[PDB]
Length: 220
Ligand SMILES: Cc1nc(=O)c2cc(CN(C)c3ccc(C(=O)N[C@@H](CCC(=O)O)C(=O)O)s3)ccc2[nH]1
Image (tube, rainbow, N blue to C red; front, side):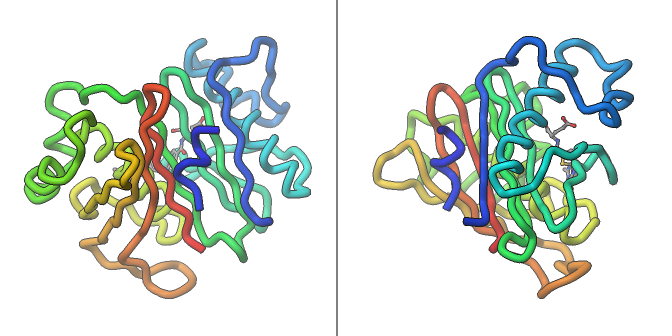
């Protein structure tokens, strides 16, 4: 699997590269996408079908995955997880809370960012430092965006505070293979959590594979 490249008996994952036809949401999930468009409908369903494959293999029976604070996914009790999707990928990674404090993942196509995006999602330092050490064959701007989204998704559940794109400083290192590596996200705002020790440094992994950028953060 692709997501295995960016992950370190309490963690499961599942991914699919297309929308399997005929899949249907759970009954009390249905009103969430009654008015949604077809393309949104498919990835809503496919990613929750991936989520329940992983959740079942952690002895958790299928349960509805609703959306809460700023659309945040909701999980069965004692559970945490993360959902992601893009043009050719649907994936979920889930974990039990005591072993996994939080999960954050993202998947993106390995293409240049649309015009004007690199500036909103990034700091003057990240833009000077990343081109010095990232391999020439990589879209460091897109990989930066993927790492940014994977950080807020792992950050937000533990603080329920909004993490702007310029409240996190991400530094990258490239593994000797050249297409994979890992990063450190440093929080520039208060790291007060609702529970647990403060959180200011998040370590995650990044990978480029099959034309796709994958990132994941697992906070033990
Ligand atoms: C810049 C920024 N900072 C934040 O802290 C932030 C927080 C949220 C709230 N949050 C934590 C989430 C909202 C949506 C999620 C998610 O995992 N979406 C999946 C599945 C969506 C679905 O099918 O319902 C996805 O992107 O596919 S996670 C959303 C955008 C943010 N953006």
